[PDB]
Image (cartoon, rainbow over the protein chains, first blue to last red):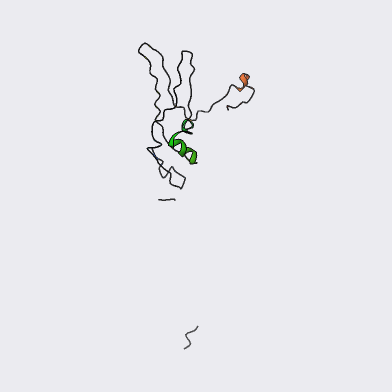
Length: 9
Length: 108
């Protein structure tokens, strides 16, 4: 009731 | 052949002129005598300061090329003699070491 709790080209 | 990707370590792409640097260069015309001993040419030191190949070798740190050496010696059919035209890899020059072998001299 709260709902807050490798180099390439 | 050109260096493969596996063999090459440098990451920058090299330049391949291939028509300005891959061509026959005529070095010199050393005279063969009856008492001649022989000569050696170091590669690519021979092509270091001439041609587009020379400019590319001077401008670039890294170099890789094959070579097509065409040694020419024309003589008549009444002349005789044979030359050993050979390619010696890593031809390190030694000295006489002062003749007696106790000088540790190095070639210039």
